Length: 216
Length: 217
Ligand SMILES: Cc1cc2nc3c(=O)[nH]c(=O)nc-3n(C[C@H](O)[C@H](O)[C@H](O)COP(=O)(O)O)c2cc1C
Ligand SMILES: Cc1cc2nc3c(=O)[nH]c(=O)nc-3n(C[C@H](O)[C@H](O)[C@H](O)COP(=O)(O)O)c2cc1C
Ligand SMILES: NC(=O)N/N=C/c1ccc([N+](=O)[O-])o1
Ligand SMILES: NC(=O)N/N=C/c1ccc([N+](=O)[O-])o1
Image 1 (cartoon, each protein chain N blue to C red):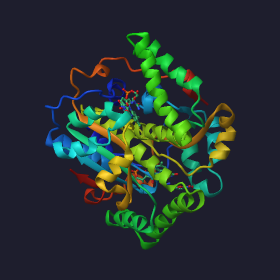
Image 2 (image 1 turned 180 degrees about the vertical axis):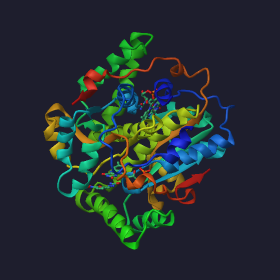
Image 3 (image 1 turned 120 degrees about the vertical axis):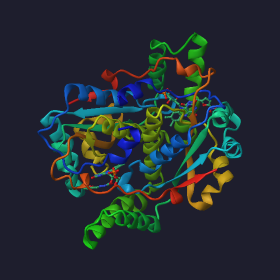
Image 4 (image 1 turned 180 degrees about the horizontal axis):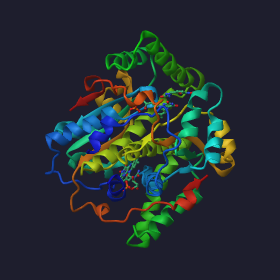
């Protein structure tokens, strides 16, 4: 079941470059990215899915300097997902989200739509006008998406590794993200592990629940 | 179902049936999901409060105050309610705890492997706690990743849930003495079975189209 998946998945340290996702799997990973929940359904994100050699090479430019030992993961995997967050929460995006919810038939009346918009703005304004942490708030939603994604891809029988060891300034510049209103946060190569993936057979290790978990 | 079915079917439950409890097996399963989430460097910079008694849930629900009152019943009515907390600072005792646990579990072939893993972990941790002074946000991001893993996992178990940011973290922290223990509350997730008042159970899901959010290269 899903608990078996959670207990058996791992962060892949080396990919077999001959092993590709099926077209079906490639569509399934896009669906996972799209259907993640987020605060107010704000979906404050953009994904770059690199599957060509040229595309993956562009992403791998970010595995520079002290991050060079992540480069092969980006090159050898089948599909490499760059998770990006918006850099500021703007009204046009808030309108885009509520209009999409309306198109999907979530509102019975104009009043219901207006109440949803008002509630979304309560949370958005708390972050972007009061706390001034909307960049962080949106980034947190993207990390939530990554968590959904890693479990989902494992459940599809695919290997992956989440990567923070990359140069986001290089990756942003490579895809012109800043000027488009986004910034790169996590890179996740997806594919099938190779024999060089020493982590595939190592035991999982987590802190005991008697440290991390209180029942009340 | 496959996992894509779960992703397409799950929803944020707006009202729970307080008579429908998790089985003992399910209660163990949700704790496993919390524990086994990945995180940057396996830093696991988190604490979970799992409230299953009516007394415990009532206390968590004290945080649904003021502008957050319309999340109160979700917290009272679900079988189990999980409070996801992050560490407020990444200290060296914790970094040692994590590498010592990895060693106990058998991840290192030699003392040199263990040292190299420790060195690599500190490379990342020090970038945040020393260069950028943003380790609190870095750790909070790992907690959000855990929440994403959790919501999909509990849905795949056939359980309803809702992630909640609409709560007063000052009240919740004080209620469980979190700050003085070195933690702060970020997300509350009631888990159980929806009630007849869950208007969201039958509404269509809505997401932005991929032509807006997704570029293939
Ligand atoms: C946000 C995030 C960033 C990570 N960055 C890297 C990375 O740059 N390179 C790498 O090899 N592993 C990376 N990892 C993998 C972690 O070390 C791994 O998740 C952790 O040790 C737990 O092991 P598991 O993923 O096999 O369960 C990262 C994980 C997360 C969650
Ligand atoms: C971090 C986070 C916090 C949220 N906070 C609340 C909340 O306080 N109350 C609530 O009813 N729903 C909350 N939601 C639910 C979102 O509105 C919901 O995830 C989004 O509309 C997408 O719908 P779905 O979860 O049904 O797919 C939150 C979701 C996330 C991810
Ligand atoms: N943040 C969200 O996604 N949605 N929040 C919904 C609600 C409903 C009641 C409250 N509340 O804060 O009382 O937040
Ligand atoms: N951040 C992590 O969890 N683990 N990182 C592992 C590695 C391995 C190589 C690199 N790197 O940055 O080149 O990071």
